Image (cartoon, rainbow, N blue to C red; front, side, top):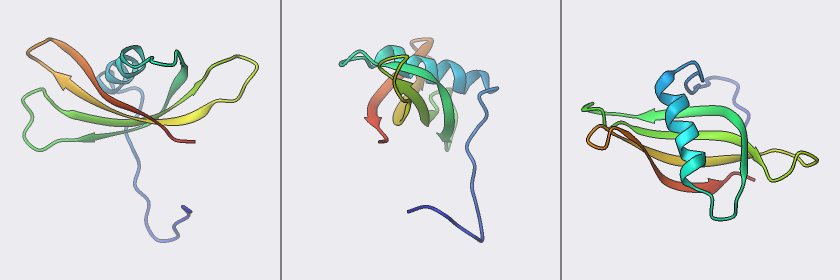
Length: 95
């Protein structure tokens, strides 16, 4: 049950070229049940020493039909420089 009244932390903007490429890659990598992501909602990045292998964690909106609701989903993504692309760690539903 969220709802703070002292402090609040925010994620990153979709404007971020890394977050947008890594987010999109997340949806295109996971599709065991064939779902559709309406778009990026929120995001987070975990880093310590960056060698272009940064860890990404974000929440987005996705639905299986245009006549249905969009729910939240939390996916973990890994960025790789050696492969020159993005990677999807895991896909989890937030509803």
